[PDB]
Amino acid sequence: DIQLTQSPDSLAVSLGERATINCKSSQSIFRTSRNKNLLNWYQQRPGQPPRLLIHWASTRKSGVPDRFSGSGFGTDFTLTITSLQAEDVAIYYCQQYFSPPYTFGQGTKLEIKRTVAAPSVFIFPPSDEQLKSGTASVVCLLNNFYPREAKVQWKVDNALQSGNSQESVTEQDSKDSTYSLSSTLTLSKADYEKHKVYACEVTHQGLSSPVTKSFNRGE
Amino acid sequence: EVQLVESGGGLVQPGGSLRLSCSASGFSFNSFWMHWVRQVPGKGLVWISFTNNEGTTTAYADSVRGRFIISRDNAKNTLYLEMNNLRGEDTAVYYCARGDGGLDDWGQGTLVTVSSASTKGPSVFPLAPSSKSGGTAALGCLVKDYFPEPVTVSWNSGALTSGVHTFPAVLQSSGLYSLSSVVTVPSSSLGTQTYICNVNHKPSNTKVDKKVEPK
Ligand SMILES: [Cl-]
């Protein structure tokens, strides 16, 4: 099997700047008879199928912007992206088409660097319908922030919570380069009904100081 | 348009068998190599198999050789992957792709989940907008306690797409998935505009339309 190693694994590049992604093949993938290095580059945007950018190491597929260019010979290949756009947020994969199995690199995850953007914070009490079932889910939403790093603490009657929440984060948006994040606090109905004040405290670079959103159970 | 459409994916017991189909249109099917590639959700592309134009040459990744069989029906414009003796490590989105210079015109993919766990439909709960972000309100749906993936969430039957965030599912301590779909809208719309999340969990035949009302 031919092994392809990409570097780096993660790359953060600002809008308008240049990204360099390398692919090292464990053996030559130059087919003499076709006079081609049989390397493909793909872009896979969040929640989308892969898109072919380049084949034969340096031939751009019709409709792919000239911002994308492939170079290299033998075992060392490079994808260069000039004038980085918001819509370039993706994982980039190299693949050899020289000898089966037609192996992929491990991928390079491209982050778009943009200006700091504070999250909008929203809290949602559990629904009456859910409380009937014996469980309380409290949700804290951090909407459209940058960068990714964010701290979310749950406080119930000012007791800091541990072990009883899960976070989920969107991929960077293709247009505004922001993240959104959900923190869900799960309590038994009984535990929920023993406390009054439910609070979500958010720390992020874009905020002057931590922001708290809270509600009083039954108000 | 070149169109590839994968089907036949779903929940299957370890040791079981599945047959994926890829329906090809908008090109001369018998003129091109065809490929299967898979991706474990949140992981990388793994090449699985290909066939030449007539199906006289085929190859397979090491981890599936002897268990999977690629084939094609050039008369019916269909590629197949027969998958036998399935294991947990075969759980992935399976893509078909047309070979030209590289792999092109990838389909949306079909999810294969190899698990002995039971199908369970989600409970859908509203995330209601309340009397407070200035001119912007958030609302949503909590889609809780389902197996397997995936669930799809649309808003107002696909008419509301701006400001929608459907979060990745988290696996809970129970081994059931949970996710939220949220949307930000003008506060000005809350009094007059109806907001309904359309949740579909096809593996359990669970379709829910949940109206989310300001409270
Ligand atoms: Cl691979």
Image (cartoon, rainbow, N blue to C red):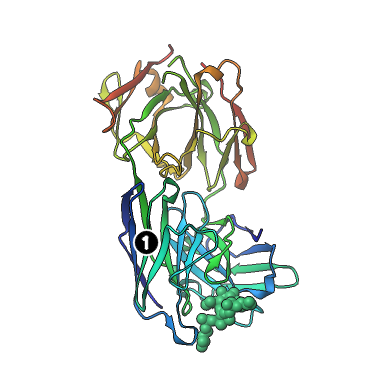
- Residue under the image location 43 percent in, 60 percent down: A68
Tell me if residue A201 comes above or below residue A47 in the rendering: above
Residue lying farthest to the left in this orientation: A209
Check the picture and name the quadrant holding the C terminus of chain A. Answer: top left
Asked if residue B86 shows in the view, the reply is no
Q: Is residue A122 above or below residue B90?
A: above
Residue A47 image offset from top left, x and y in percent: 50, 49
Q: Amino acid at mark 1?
A: Thr
Residue A173: x %, y % from top left: 44, 42
Residue extending furthest right? B75
Would you say A28 lies left or right of B75 here?
left
| SS type, badge 1 | strand
- Pinpoint residue B40: horizontal percent, then vertical percent: 46, 57
Residue named by callout 1: A80
The answer to whether B110 appears left or right of A209 in the picture is right
